[PDB]
Image (cartoon, rainbow over all chains, first blue to last red; front, top):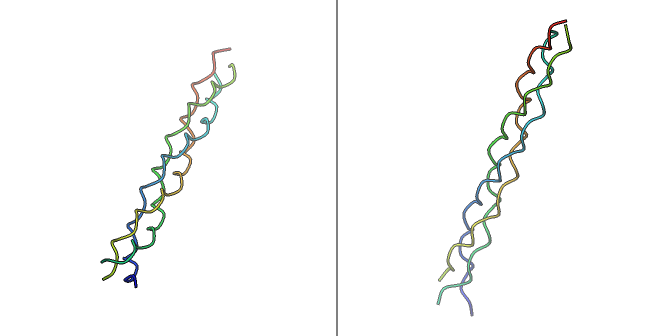
Length: 30
Length: 30
Length: 30
């Protein structure tokens, strides 16, 4: 009958880059 | 002959942090 | 004998959102 399963495979690739952050705060009064 | 391939590896690390957001809106008029 | 290593894991989660962008420019003069 078949031999034992092999070792676990390696870790996956990193996820995709995160989303751009939100807009910054409004500038100061002119 | 060799047994079955091992189990699939774990999920990878998180992706790189996202870029900084767009510049904020201009301030109010002086 | 034991099988070959398993397949590579799935991708990690998406990166975190970036930080808020730079502050806006100063408003126009009154």
